[PDB]
Structure formats: structure tokens, C-alpha cells
Image: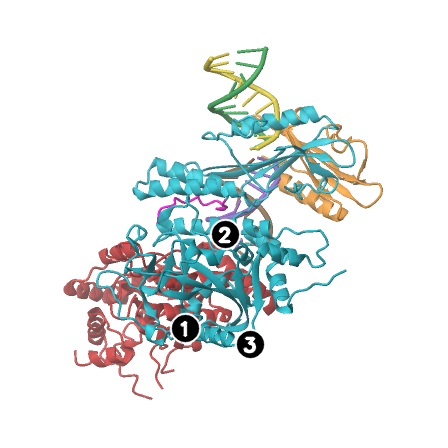
Chain colours: A red, B cyan, C orange, D yellow, E green, F brown, G purple
Amino acid sequence: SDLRKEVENHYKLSLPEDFYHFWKFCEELDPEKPSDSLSASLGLQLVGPYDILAGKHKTKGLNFNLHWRFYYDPPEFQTIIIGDNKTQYHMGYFRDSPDEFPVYVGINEAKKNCIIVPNGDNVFAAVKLFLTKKLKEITDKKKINLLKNIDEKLTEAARELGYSLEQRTVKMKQRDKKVVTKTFHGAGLVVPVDKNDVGYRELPETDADLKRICKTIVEAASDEERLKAFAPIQEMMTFVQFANDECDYGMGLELGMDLFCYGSHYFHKVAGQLLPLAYNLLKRNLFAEIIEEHLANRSQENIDQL
Amino acid sequence: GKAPVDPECTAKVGKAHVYCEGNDVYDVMLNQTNLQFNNNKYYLIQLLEDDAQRNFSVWMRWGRVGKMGQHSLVACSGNLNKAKEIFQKKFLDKTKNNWEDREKFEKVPGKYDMLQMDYKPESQLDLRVQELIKLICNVQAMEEMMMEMKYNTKKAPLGKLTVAQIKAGYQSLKKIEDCIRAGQHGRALMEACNEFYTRIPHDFGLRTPPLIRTQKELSEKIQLLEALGDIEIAIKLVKTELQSPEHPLDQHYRNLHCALRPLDHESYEFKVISQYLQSTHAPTHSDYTMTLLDLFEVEKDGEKEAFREDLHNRMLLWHGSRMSNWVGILSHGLRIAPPEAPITGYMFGKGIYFADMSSKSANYCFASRLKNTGLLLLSEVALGQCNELLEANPKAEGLLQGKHSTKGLGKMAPSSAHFVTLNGSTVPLGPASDTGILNPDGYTLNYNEYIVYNPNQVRMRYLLKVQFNFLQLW
Amino acid sequence: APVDPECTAKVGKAHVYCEGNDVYDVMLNQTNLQFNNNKYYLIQLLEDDAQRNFSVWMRWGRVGKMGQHSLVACSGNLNKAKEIFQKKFLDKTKNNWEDREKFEKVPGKYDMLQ
DNA sequence: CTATGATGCC
DNA sequence: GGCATCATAG
DNA sequence: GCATGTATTG
DNA sequence: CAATACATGC
């Protein structure tokens, strides 16, 4: 516990206990380099707060909101494991608010798409799912025994700690009932909703039509053509103002997120006007900080120890 | 009124006219929808006789509303009798109603329903009012906005509507409100939704038309219908006039029937209004600024006698709207929502809505980067005793019991300590500050707003010409 | 390969365009007793005398009966008319118009009248 | 949807 | 006979 | 990224 | 049939 508080003080976020227990698990597997204990076997790397666990942050300006923050990792998303650097495959805890625990572990390929795929509710589940999926992907049999042994250790540790190993747990299916919309990232929004349905309202445009709007705007051949084409974004932003004035904050939360998912620099400012404010209105100030810093410095290489 | 021919009939748009006989104009649009079986289709029919040569034709065109479709042109070489017969027969087949007595129309289930359509210069005026009128009286811009109301935002794909068609739409929204009020999502709700989507043409692409299930969609539909009515009144008002005007806008100005006088920038009134504009820019609407370019004095006939001067608590409050519809207000003043409109769309009831924070009302102007000119109107409103509301309750109007207006208690708002006076009316200067109203049970309204019910309690006083200045975009 | 008299909206006042092999007038038939398909489709390009002002006629239905028809006007340019004609022929037959000579009846697509 | 055609109804 | 619920075909 | 097989509606 | 769109593999 004595090495936990410095970790969580650095991130301004609380980390669940499975994170630290998995640290101890990997330490027992390989005391010399626990973070990379699965790197020789799986090609995966423990990073982020594990970097603090490894003491590798002691080489040093250190901005942890960007540490391994991939191009499409939403502020809700805290990268914890890296895989293929060609596709920027990675796994991370997903937190809807800075005061809550992660709801599950998601995976994304930042060079492939913006979709975050649920991968269990804890890192044991995430690594087991990746391991099992690769076991069939691996075109060999001799080089599998090591994976069987490490997987055996994974299963026994999860059983001893009382963790379910399902890809989708009970708590995730409960959150999904609280999930109000997928918002191009597929992970769902959690916003306050009172007994009069106050707190959220849907966008004036469908998701497919929103993606079409983004395509037609980003592909405009001149800035004058964009300004003429910009009319639907301006309209949607005015209605977003209307909604926030009536406490339906999540709408302004969602629209910016879609632009965050779209990825074009032409939308960096407008999202910076929508997403931070929405987080401020939602009292998620840390996410406003994260989105400000990421939009100002959204890079394709993000290991702060380089 | 003026009877236009469908332009899509290129072979006959310039050589032919729609047929008319007194009341009966042989032109008709039918709509059908059934979300149970996911039908959403239109059918237009028009009898056209050529202008030059004596030859009649029936034009039919059909498809999904919004998406242009299959058409047919049947020529008759002047066989007007046969052509009229065919017209009436098809009208009956598709509607189960006879065409000639179109007056008594009765839609039947599983058949198309009808709808109703609209088918020596000494220009003496101040130059500033001239610019204002030309800005608001620009017919081109009204046409362009109407075309945008069909091909930009598909709210009225096929065309326009009549006042009475809108009223029937409101009737259907009332039936929807009644249905939804009991939370029953079975068959009657689906039929009521069918009636709504029949009366007001929508385009859903292919995705089954969804059920209207919550209050938010009700209110959005209500605002759409309101915008339809606004466009209708704007085109009615912009009717051009002859008789030696030498500046037709002067007759348009008479149609405003509202004195609008230019104010000097150095006058106390102009400076104070600028102070009020600037001091009350909410901090959470920071994507743009606003500059006061010019300010006009308002004198609307008949309002003076109506003002509730006896009532206390008189303040100057904002009212924003798009550049184009202002022509209607200056001619007719602000109106309460229509009687037939569903009450449950307005979380605190019907009436006239005002803010005291410039940017909150200003959000209703929809100004743009390309089109940077918007207007905000200031009106003196005698609120009298306000009824205090913490949480949404659409039934606020019954709770008045002697009060004259409702106040929705927002988190951020000016405090009366900073209030000043203008011509004996209270001017609520900002900045906004915390008001110590909070809710230990539910949400908290972001900002106050004040609503009045008697139309006689509003007196428009100045019209503000405002440059909305947007900023960097990436 | 006569101009259809049944096209009352166009008979009398124009001459169908062709070019040797490439005859932009044709009637296609498809019979298929398994599915009780028996349908025809005529296509005809017509030129104005005064100006280069063309029209594409399509007519289709169950054999013998006029069924339905469509007039797509191409006063703009005859090349547009060739585009519509040839593209539609490919869509409807899976055979190109330039290669129409080597026709191979694929199932469920039109063949022409020899 | 055109559009004929069909049975079955009145 | 005549019209219409209905087919299905295109 | 390209064209289109297919299902769906007028 | 038109006609539009949505999954459809190389």
C-alpha cells in the first residue's frame, strides 16, 4: 500500500486493487522486469502507472494525462498495456468519472479505428482474452507450452483473488442499462439522469449522418467551402448550448466526443469548446484538463520516458 | 393565391399552367405512413393545360417523401373531360374520397391522406432604418431559408403548408400528448404516431419511423412546427406592393406599422444598452462575442394602452430570434403558444419567454460566421409577483394564484444590488453571480428565466443591431 | 427495328439515332417459366431536327401489354444519352454495349431480338 | 408505385 | 354488371 | 476503395 | 420496373 499512494497522487486518479495485485503477480513471475514479464512471451508491455511501479519515471516536465495516451484514447480511457506498435494495439482501464473505479478494461488499435472493444472488467480478463485469441492466431504448437504455463498461473491467481474471467461481467451488463449512447466509440456515456429524464437529450442528427457530415466537411476543397459547409456544426452547437442551459449536459458531452473520434485538426477547437465545458458542467474537471492538454498536444508517439 | 406549376415537369414548366376553377384547383398532395408496417410515401397529382396549345395532361409523381421519385405525364390532346375523369378516379382510388367534393375530406386507415399547400424615387427614410428594413425585408434570403428548410434540414421536403394544416398538425400533437401521458406503448400509440407522421412530412431514409416516446421529442416537434408557422407568416408579410412606392420597402415598413428610430451612439440610452449587452454576456457562451453596431427605438401601435402599468417589478428583458422572422414580430408583437399546442412540451407552460442575460436569449439568434448579423430585442415586461420554481413542472400556470409571472430559479444570475434604471424601468446589470439557490433533491436550473402570460404585459422598446463575432475554429 | 407507335408522346416528330452496328434502338425479351417471368423492354434514342436535342425512351412490361414507360430527356448532350443507354444496357444484361455482338445469356437478364 | 389482373363480393 | 380487397409482377 | 448483389419501397 | 441504400467481398 505504501507504494500505491504515490502512484495515485501522480495521476490524480484512483486505481483498482486488481492493478496492484497484477503487479505483484508479474513481480513473482519475473522480479527483474515485472512489467515486461509477458513481453518475451506475448509481446505485450505493462506501462502507465506500472511505469511508476517500475520506478522507470526516475530518469527525469512530466504530463501523465498524455503518457501513452494514444490518438483516439478518450479522456475516460487510461492506457495500461501496450501490444503491437504497428497497429498501436493497447488495453486500458475505462473510467467514466475521476472519482470512480474503472468499469472494465477496453482495447483499441489507434492506427486502425476509433472503436474501444470491451475486454473484461479487470486486467486478468483482458490478458486472458488476448492470450486465448492469440493461441489460435499463433501458427505453431511447440511454442505454446510457455503460454499454457503462464495462462495456468493467470487462472490460479484469478481464482485465488475471486475475480470472474468472463469477457463481459455482471457489472458491465448493469452499466450497459445505464449506458445512454455509444457515441462512435462504442463504450457508452454515463450521465446524471433524474426522475424527470433531465440530464440528456439526443443529437439532432443520426450517427451515420453525423459521420457523413464529418466526411463532407473534412473533405471540402477550400476553407470557404468548409465555412459554407460548416452550417450544420454551428446549428448543432447552438442546440447544444440550448441543451446545456436546461441541464442536458451529456448532449454537449457526446457531440465533442464524436469530433474527438473523427480525428481531424479542423475540429480541435470546437471540441475544445464543447468537451471541456461539458466535463466542467458535469463536475469532471480532471477530464477537462486531460482533453485540453491532449487537444493541444495530440501526438502519435506518447511514451513520456521515450 | 398565386398558383405555381411544379418546376420538375421541364417539358411543361414554361408552356403550361395548373388548372383552376374558382375554389377548386386541380392540384393535390397525398401522404401516407404506417410505422407498424413501415410505410412512408407521398403522391403528388397535378392537372396541367398548356398555355400555347389546347392540350391537357395529368402529371403524377410518387416516392418516398424527400427522395424524388417515379413520374408519369399523360397527354390528352385537349380531352379535358377524360383527363378530369382519370384525375378524380385516381384521387378516389388513393384516398377513398371523391375529388370534386374535396371540401369534405375524410381519411381512412391504410390509404393516403390529403394535405393542403400554398400552390420619381425620393426614398425618404433614415439610412440606418433603410439598411435594417432591406436586411429583414430581403425576399431572396427568405426564399433561400425556405429552400434550406427542405434540402438542408429535411423538415418540409415536399414544400410549404397552410396555417390550417399546421393547426391540424397541432391537433395530432395533442392526441400524441394525451396518448403519451399514460405511458402506454401499444397499438393506439403507434396509430397516433402514424397520424402525426401523416400530417407533417418527415424523411427517415429507411430506418422504421421511431415512436415518439419522451417529452424532448415532443418539444422538438413543437419547435419545428413553430418554425413552419414562422416561415408562413414571414412570407405572408413580405408581400410586395405597387402604387408608386418609389421604395417598396416603405410600404413594407407601413406593414411593420411600428416606428423604428435611429439612435445616436453617444446618447445615454445607446451607451447604457451597450453596457447591459456586455455586462450580461454569460461566461459559458464564450465561443463568440457580440458587438452593438446600432440601436433603434421601438414604438409599436396599440401596445401603450395594453401595458399593465399598474403592476410592479418592471424590467427590461431580452428576446432573440433568427434575422428573418423579426418582420413578423414588429408587425404583430409577441404571441402566446397556440391553444391547440400540447401543454407538456413547455416544461413551465405556455406564454412569452424572456431572459435578463443577453447571451442566453442571444443563443436563439442562430447567427453564423458567414452571416454575422443578428438582432436582439429588448422589451419592458411587468413581471409583477413571480412564482418561484425549483424543478420542472409543466403545470406552473395553475400555481399562479394571484401572481402574474413565473420565475425559473437558475444557478447563475445577477443580484438586484447592481440594478440600475432606464426611463423608470429596472435594468438588471450583471455580472452573474451565485444566488444561493440549490436543490438537495434533484437538479438545479442553470440560469433564471422569466415567463409572462398576459400578452398585454410586454412593451417592446428598443431593437438592437448586433454583430456576432466568432473566433478561431481549429 | 421500328420506332414504337405506342410512344404517343414521341411518335411523328423525330428520327431514332443509330450508328451501323451500334443501333440505339432495341427490344429485349426475357422469358423464364420457372418464375413466370415474361417481360420485354424497348429502348429508343430520338433526335430533334433543329438542335442537338435528344430523348431516351424506355418501355417495359409483360409481353404484349404496354405496362410502364419512362422518358429521360437529354437536350443537354447526345453523349449523356449514350451514357444512359449503354450503362442501362449493362445494368440490365451484364453485357457491354460495345461488346453487344458477343451476347451470352446469363440467367435472369435480358436477351435481345435477333 | 403502374398496372393489369384476379377472385370474390355487392 | 360493376367494383373492389388483393397479387403479384414488373 | 471499387463496383454490385440484394433487400425494400414506391 | 425505378430507385436508394447497405452490406459485399478482393
- Same chain for the residues under marks 1 and 3 in the image: yes
Looking at the image, which is closer to me, C16 or A255? A255
- Provide the residue designation for mark 3: B265
- Provide the residue designation for mark 2: B227
Looking at the image, which is closer to me, A142 or B55? B55
- What's the distance in space between the residues labelled 1 and 3, CA to CA? 19 Å
Q: Amino acid at mark 2?
A: Ala
Looking at the image, which is closer to me, B164 or B107? B164
**Image quarter in which the N terminus of chain B is found:** top right
* Above/below status of A256 relative to B452: below
* Mark 2 Cα shell of 10 Å, populated few (<14), some (14-19), many (≥20): some
Give how far across and how far down residue B427 sits, in percent. 41, 71
Which of the numbered marks, if any, corresponds to residue B421?
1
Residue C82 is one of the magenta-drawn residues? no
- Report the residue at 24% width, 64% height from top: B439
Residue B206 is one of the magenta-drawn residues? yes
Give how far across and how far down residue B345 sits, in percent. 38, 50
**Disc nearest the viewer among 3 and 2:** 3
| In this rendering, position of residue B331 left or right of residue A72 | right
Chain at tag 3 = B
